[PDB]
Amino acid sequence: AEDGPQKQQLEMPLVLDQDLTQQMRLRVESLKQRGEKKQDGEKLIRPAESVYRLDFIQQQKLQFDHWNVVLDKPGKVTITGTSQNWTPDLTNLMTRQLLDPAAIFWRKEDSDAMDWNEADALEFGERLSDLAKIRKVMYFLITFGEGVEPANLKASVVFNQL
Ligand SMILES: C[As](C)(=O)[O-]
Ligand SMILES: [Zn+2]
Ligand SMILES: [Zn+2]
Ligand SMILES: [Zn+2]
Ligand SMILES: [Zn+2]
Ligand SMILES: [Zn+2]
Ligand SMILES: [Zn+2]
């Protein structure tokens, strides 16, 4: 097999999850207004982070091909996946539930080309095929650097269908 254009591929977008993001925002706020301490080991959402969602329209016979992360303005974004054991409806995200490594993408000033941490972005992507088997939905925390917001970002993952 030689890698080529005629391969069945599926592109699955990472969609902003407003209500989960809002739920997490509220959580940090409540903790302040009440002067309460966060849970032992909890991950509190920083204002620059937003929760994204990826719905595996197919879970079996998937092979990670590449990331399709694009910024329409110079900037930087970090995409950190979360454990497939974290069910947002049930618990507050734990720091240990953040997957290592994260995929970091950036666009420098006068160039239009994106660049990223190739080795880690690949390692992370390879994991998605197995994570899809655990459940149809997966959550991510996308950290936006200075100058960029969710509106500037278009992220998706491309899998070759086996
Ligand atoms: C925490 As929700 C209501 O985005 O499944
Ligand atoms: Zn070859
Ligand atoms: Zn939601
Ligand atoms: Zn839910
Ligand atoms: Zn590079
Ligand atoms: Zn590099
Ligand atoms: Zn690394």
Image (cartoon, grey):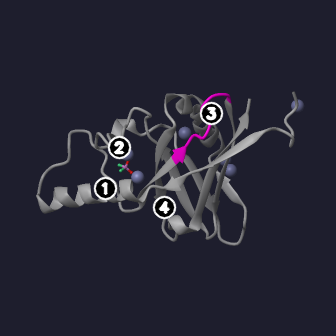
Quadrant of image for the C terminus: top right
Answer with mark 3 or mark 4, whichever residue precedes in sequence. Answer: 3
Q: Which amino acid is tagged 1?
A: Gln
- The image quadrant that residue 55 belongs to is top right
Residue 51, how many percent across, how many down?
43, 53
- Give the extent of the magenta segment: 54-61
88 relative position to 143: left or right: left
Image point (61%, 42%), residue name: 121
Q: Is mark 1 within 8 Å of ligand 1?
A: yes
Majority SS type along the magenta span = loop
Residue 26: x and y, percent? 26, 59
Q: Indicate which disc residue 88 carries.
A: 2
Which residue appears at 88% of the width and 31% of the height? 2
The answer for how far apart the CA atoms under marks 3 and 2 are is 24 Å
Q: Position of residue 73 (x, y in %)?
A: 61, 71
Disc 4 to disc 1, C-alpha distance:
19 Å
Q: Residue 134 in the image: state x and y as whole percent.
A: 49, 29
**Around disc 4, counting alpha carbons within 10 Å, would you say few (fewer than 14), some (14 to 19), or many (20 or more)?**
many
Does the stretch in magenta take in 55? yes
The residues bearing labels 3 and 4 have C-alpha atoms spaced at a distance of 23 Å
Confirm or deny contact between disc 1 and disc 2 (CB under 8 A): yes
Query: Element under label 1?
Result: helix
How far apart in space, not on screen, are marks 1 and 2 (Cα)?
9 Å
Amino acid at dot 2: Pro
Residue annotated with mark 1: 23
Labels 4 and 1: the sequence-earlier one:
1
Q: Is mark 2 within 8 Å of ligand 1?
A: yes
Which residue bears the numbered disc 3?
126
In the picture of the structure, the residue carrying the numbered disc 4 is 144
On screen, residue 56 above or below 114 = above
